[PDB]
Amino acid sequence: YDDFMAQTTTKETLATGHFMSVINILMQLRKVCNHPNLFDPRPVTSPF
Amino acid sequence: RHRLSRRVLLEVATAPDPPPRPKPVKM
Amino acid sequence: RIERIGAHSHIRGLGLDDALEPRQASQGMVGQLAARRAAGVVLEMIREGKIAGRAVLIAGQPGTGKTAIAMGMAQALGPDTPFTAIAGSEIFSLEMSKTEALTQAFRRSIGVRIKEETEIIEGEVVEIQIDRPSKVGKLTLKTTEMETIYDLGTKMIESLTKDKVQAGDVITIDKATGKISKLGRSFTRARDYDAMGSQTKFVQCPDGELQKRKEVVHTVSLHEIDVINSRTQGFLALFSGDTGEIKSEVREQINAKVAEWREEGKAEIIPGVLFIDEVHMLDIESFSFLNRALESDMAPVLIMATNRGITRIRGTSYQSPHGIPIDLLDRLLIVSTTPYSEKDTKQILRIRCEEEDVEMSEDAYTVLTRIGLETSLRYAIQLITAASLVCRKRKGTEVQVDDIKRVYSLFLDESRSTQYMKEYQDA
Amino acid sequence: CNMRTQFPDLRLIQYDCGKLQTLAVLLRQLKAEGHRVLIFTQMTRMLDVLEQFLTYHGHLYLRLDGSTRVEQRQALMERFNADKRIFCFILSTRSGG
Amino acid sequence: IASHSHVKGLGLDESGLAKQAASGLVGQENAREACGVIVELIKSKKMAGRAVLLAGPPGTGKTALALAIAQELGSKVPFCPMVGSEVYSTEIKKTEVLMENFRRAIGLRIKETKEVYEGEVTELTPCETENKTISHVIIGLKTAKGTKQLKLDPSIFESLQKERVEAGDVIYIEANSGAVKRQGRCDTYATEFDLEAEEYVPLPKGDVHKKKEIIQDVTLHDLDVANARPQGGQDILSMMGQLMKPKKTEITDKLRGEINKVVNKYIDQGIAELVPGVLFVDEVHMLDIECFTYLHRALESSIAPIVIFASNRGNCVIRGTEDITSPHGIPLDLLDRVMIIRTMLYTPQEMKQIIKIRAQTEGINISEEALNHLGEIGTKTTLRYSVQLLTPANLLAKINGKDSIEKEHVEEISELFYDAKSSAKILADQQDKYM
Amino acid sequence: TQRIASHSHVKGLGLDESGLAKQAASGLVGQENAREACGVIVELIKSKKMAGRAVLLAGPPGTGKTALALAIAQELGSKVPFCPMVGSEVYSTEIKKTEVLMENFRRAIGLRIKETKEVYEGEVTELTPCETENPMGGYGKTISHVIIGLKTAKGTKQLKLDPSIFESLQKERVEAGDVIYIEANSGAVKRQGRCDTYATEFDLEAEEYVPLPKGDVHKKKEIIQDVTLHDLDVANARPQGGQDILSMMGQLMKPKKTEITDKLRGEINKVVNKYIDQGIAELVPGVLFVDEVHMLDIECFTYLHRALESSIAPIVIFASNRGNCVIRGTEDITSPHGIPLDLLDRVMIIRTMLYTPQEMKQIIKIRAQTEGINISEEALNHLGEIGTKTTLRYSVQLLTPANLLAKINGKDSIEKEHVEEISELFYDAKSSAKILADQQ
Amino acid sequence: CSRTFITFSDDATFEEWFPQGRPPKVPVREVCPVTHRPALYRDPVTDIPYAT
Ligand SMILES: Nc1ncnc2c1ncn2[C@@H]1O[C@H](COP(=O)(O)OP(=O)(O)O)[C@@H](O)[C@H]1O
Ligand SMILES: Nc1ncnc2c1ncn2[C@@H]1O[C@H](COP(=O)(O)OP(=O)(O)O)[C@@H](O)[C@H]1O
Ligand SMILES: Nc1ncnc2c1ncn2[C@@H]1O[C@H](COP(=O)(O)OP(=O)(O)O)[C@@H](O)[C@H]1O
């Protein structure tokens, strides 16, 4: 949530957007607020 | 006992040994 | 079955009430009211468990119930909470350092419990049928209420064959993993017994639903997770204490993972107790480590006991009370046990011979209390059993004064021994 | 295998999600009373993870969508409105509500 | 669960001046703003091997301050807590413990891309050829968004066999690692048998072959260890990580050499960022004279972290010398190389408000009369002891049915338990009874 | 027979039914008080009820501490474990001191486990299945039993097993005319080899042409195996087996080997309790004997506090020699017997006395009797007289060399001349000390 | 009861693997034609058994 809400592109979109793009921001937030494999599945973590 | 002297190996370096004949059976 | 009565078998826990009020001689503990109440307070804080790394030192004379109080706390605390008891001299390993030994002692008394619901099939086998071909078969299972039939896949046929299970076995199937475990023979599992075979290992068959959901708990100590993650061998956890765990991303990594499990609720952290008996045996390096090992949020409470007062610390020439630096001594609450009144001595001996199942006359109690008040309590406890054996050799019913007097003459008490040591043996 | 690569659990789907954690607590507390529950959520593909979450807890349920055809909608409503032993009805806030 | 929890920052203003009571710290103004200079020294990433000594009597917050530095810095930089006593290893050289702890205080945040193949494997065939071993294995994979086919290495075939895969079940492959997992049978197959040993899982989603960028972070020590005792993955040198696997005195040739070279090579091609952190050697007063003399060369190295020492002693004998004595228990040669921060001994009012902060940190309600009494106990005995009486008194409060601590509560608790100062007279009066 | 050692003559404490000693019962003479005391502790062992009880045999060197300490072992017999260790065995390179102490502690707790096993064997002559009615649809060839005929030197008998044995038998690949083994409860079939009646006459084969078994076709016996808890512990710590590559820790010997409580207690006390409460095994708690205990470290002495206070401990006999003496590992702490006062508070002390001349003549006579020496009463009296001046042990030790002089001199028994001669060939400690004091 | 059957519902040949036959090792101690001891050897060139 705090990553997505602070990214350069999301800041820009919240500054200016033709409605639907900001609604897409808060709907991506539907995703990340309800459960995260809507937003992104947790990665497999592996040694570098 | 079975030490193979220089002699016995120079001996087996003589004319060759003949072949066998194992085919027959009689008991 | 056979764990013979030792020095502390009689105390079944601290004899406290619902208000942490110690009783005079209830629940096997006698006298020693103030220190027992203090032990009760810290036991309740162990149970509450929300504060980490708090530390208690049970100080007092030799023989005044310090170890008795510690094992009373262990017994009152019961299973399912880790109580790890260690002598201070156990941490001087050749295989690992003092401080790794102490980390492992601390971590062995924190438990991580993962609690999970899982669905099983529990039933008495009525039939098993299986064909060679990708082999294939069927299984029919019964409970007192119902029966049902299952078609079996290849892996399930394999695992059923691996246990050689058959009709009349009463078994569980874990639907998630498929491991079979015959609890025993149903009363319908009797062989033909026309020839010799397996014995009559009969047990009742199951009731209720054939498939049911039940809880399983996997509890492991923090040291146990730590070891089995340390290196791929890992049966270290039983093999021996062969360790030297890498601090780098095993302590922090386990702590973060267990904290995440705690926070998301996958696991519950159950902090326990580390009891260091004869803690004066620790090295100044060991005390220095304890200082900051206590200052952690995965630290159990640790209890300590010591017989000695003003004396030099091990590994140096610094005098200090209890033989502990006033650096670590400042992290502690100190509970001092007092010497016993004549009635407390008499009552300890009474409870102790009750534990050892030997009768004595009241004159025997009188003289033995006199012995254990002139000499030392442990010696009076040792005379109980010796006099009992002397009594039984004369086919007596109970221990009499003459038995105790005889066996007192027969064994010495370190005072009379030093008195008789007036012969300059190998000084 | 475990010591070289860590995969997401995928079994307890309530792992990352506090919403599902508090929901698990709430449903567990309500189960003692057994008076049954409607769970409304939009996001048709979120009903999927609720449908998984309830099997992890062994709750008998059924669920209603924009994709469930009409006769099945009536059948589900009848097999819940007039049938016990079902604890939970997962349904879309628009199509079911 | 708490212990040093109350403190969560140095409690400084925008001017870097101590606020007298903030962020969990309620005294030590000079020391806390000196620590402000230290945190700025750490966050600038400009210096190497600078060292700080927090010096003062026991209980004067010199660990509270050192941990509050860790909080002021955040969780983004490495903070390595260490006790001096940790150098005395059995398995590794005493000076080696120390020089590796320097290495894990330097972090490295590095971004990686690793390629994934996943899905239901719809078909498999090993490519047979004469050598007469297997050449490869061909595979086909399905996901909710597509399908593809590929050729895979014999090692990956070997690990697929370790896993015992079958046609028509779900797998995952991380090809840079070469690792494999059999994730189960597809949900669609769950009807195939009435009982099975399988676990059934819905089909993977997204592409059958995918990539993504992952910002790992490691330490220089992790790179060191990774090359000294490799896991390696694709080899049977598990035989070296086995019937041996101890700690080793890994050496300059790679530690100061190869590892530094590859890390710089990552840094100045943009793949990584170096993040110097802190090594906090607490209880430094009981390192060996060998360790102290090695810290000379360690603090003078151009790659070292910032080192915070905490010491607690007067002037006493240095461990390992047996004759020479020095302040803080540290030789003057190393004491010349550190900036010394005093920590003060608390006055009664500062001590009293530490009691209050501690009480409200673990959810204890305490009446002001009892709070004042704990202040009196604290000045009579010590801060840490009167702080410790809080939880036992709350337990007695619960047992008496109260919701807060009151005067006779702390009296009872302060009667059951003794402090170090108050136990010494008991041990001194009856001297020849305790032994 | 076997060689004569220092204590080969002691055969028991020498106690009659009231627990006294007449004067010289069963190879021990004198020490009536001490022998009565450890007569009590013998019965403390036999009652199996107590744990961690400890007794300290304290007295001057040569006063029979070791002798009656192992006379206890004779009284107990070979059934119970008697585990001797000297106070110097604790110092080790591979393993920490207190771990040696724990190993020895539960090396002294035995566990004797009784189990019948029953077996069938013989040359297998018949191997025919028994067809039966179709259990289900018409496949035919439904095997309900299998008949197997076994021959031994006693007789030939036919036996019916259920078809699972038919499968195992085939998987074991046995043939008619070879010799098998069947374990009735477990159900195993093991092929112990083709019968020797089909002899290796020109067959060179290494597979055992095993002789036709003697005795009945069916034989059962109660195996009775005694193991110490330490054997179970060690066998669990470093196990055997030709698999599980960890088991190929085979080039390596076994340092680092300090056993762990999780195993020791959590996994191994439960199985012993189970076998005991099931009727399969009996616990035989034995004795741990630690002579020269004064050699232990202060760390060891403090560990013994915890060890002796356990419920799962043997009874421990300590023997000590020193006076008031510095405890090892301490900076000049002096205490009785070289043992910390703290541990002396935990041991019943048995005091051994220093012998009279009469008792020494008796011991010398018994030692001569044991070593096979014939000695004249004059030589016996002279050995006694020179043994009053120096230690008993020297007096006793002069016997065999004096007997060798007698044999060389053609005599059948020690004449006084030979003990005189040997007493000038060899010195005791005191005489040698005087020599050393004279010359620089 | 819980009794066990194995049915060879396939071609009876699969049961026919097992039964019938069970012969002995027919030979018995052979006597040499010279010293009439029981034989220990058989000559490769004649196959005659012999002892000394
Ligand atoms: N409060 C008590 N209640 C019951 N028994 C006691 C008590 N105190 C001591 N004992 C007995 O006295 C002996 C000595 O107690 P212990 O705890 O070993 O003393 P310490 O450990 O303080 O030296 C124990 O064996 C125990 O049986
Ligand atoms: N300035 C402060 N503000 C708040 N709490 C403090 C402060 N100083 C010390 N404390 C508390 O008192 C304890 C003693 O300080 P600590 O850092 O342990 O000193 P030392 O490390 O010298 O023993 C700490 O653990 C902390 O809980
Ligand atoms: N009571 C006794 N009866 C018979 N022989 C004895 C007796 N006491 C001592 N001896 C003999 O004298 C020797 C010295 O006794 P021992 O117990 O070995 O010395 P220590 O008491 O120093 O261990 C023994 O080896 C034994 O041969």
Image (cartoon, coloured by chain):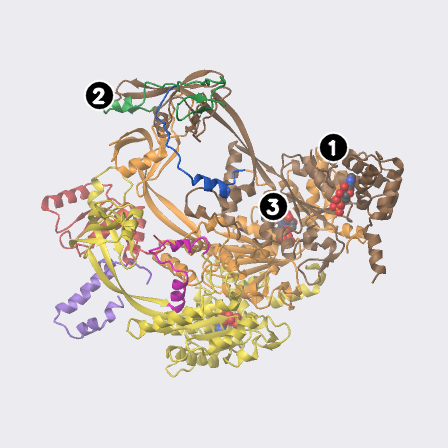
Chain colours: A purple, B blue, C orange, D red, E yellow, F brown, G green
Q: Is residue E180 left or right of residue C67?
A: left
Q: Nearer the viewer, residue E11 or F170?
A: F170
Q: Position of residue E338 (x, y in %)?
A: 50, 79
Local secondary structure at mark 2: loop
Q: Earlier in the sequence, mark 3 or mark 2?
A: 3
Q: CA distance from mark 1 to mark 3?
A: 32 Å
Local secondary structure at mark 3: helix
Label 1 chain ID: C
Q: Nearer the viewer, residue C302 or C72?
A: C302
Mark 1 or mark 3, whichever is nearer to me: 3
Q: Nearer the viewer, residue F240 or C171?
A: F240
Q: Amino acid at mark 3?
A: Phe
Instruction: Name the residue tied to disc 2.
Output: F138
Q: Is residue A40 left or right of residue F123?
A: left
Is E328 rendered above or below residue C240? below
Instruction: Name the residue tied to disc 1.
Output: C394
Q: Are marks 2 and 1 in contact (CB under 8 Å)?
A: no
Q: Position of residue E187 (x, y in %)?
A: 21, 46
Q: On residue F105, which mark appears? A: 3
Q: Position of residue E404 (x, y in %)?
A: 47, 63
Q: Amino acid at mark 1?
A: Arg
Q: Is residue F376 left or right of residue C388?
A: right
User: Residues in magenta?
Assistant: E219-244
Local secondary structure at mark 1: loop
What residue is at 37 percent from the left and 77 percent from the top? E43
Q: Amino acid at mark 2?
A: Gly
Q: CA distance from mark 3 to mark 2?
A: 67 Å
Q: Nearer the viewer, residue E12 or D94?
A: E12
What residue is at 31 percent from the left and 69 percent from the top? E110
Label 3 chain ID: F
